[PDB]
Image (cartoon, rainbow, N blue to C red; front, side, top):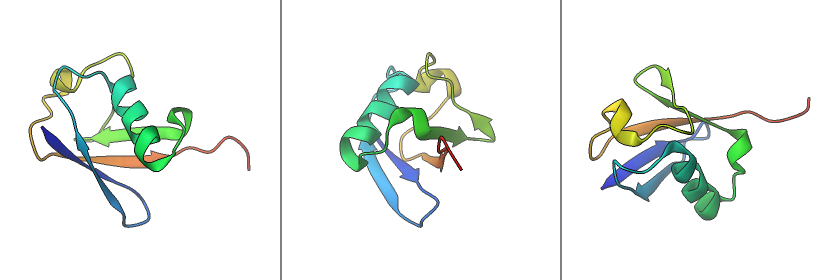
Length: 76
């Protein structure tokens, strides 16, 4: 299924995922496609911060959903 990942810069990235995919795996996909290291990634859906070990299905994330990507940089 297709999902949308909305960043803080007004860029939306499209991903192809399965509800059985883990959050850790989604983050890897994002890294693969945009180059953002997973450790800097903070995914938000329905007011919840998504946990690495959970799957998309745990959160009831359906096709064409939009996740919010917030960056957490290490150092400033």
